[PDB]
Length: 16
Image (cartoon, rainbow, N blue to C red):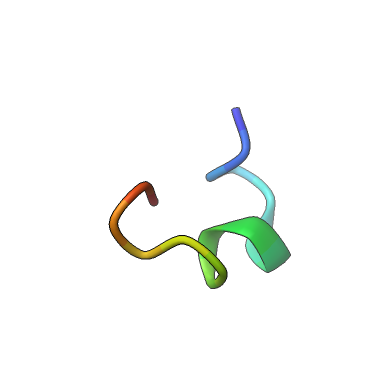
């Protein structure tokens, strides 16, 4: 998943 990746998690708060 993308939320497991820090740059993505901090990019998509609603998703992650």
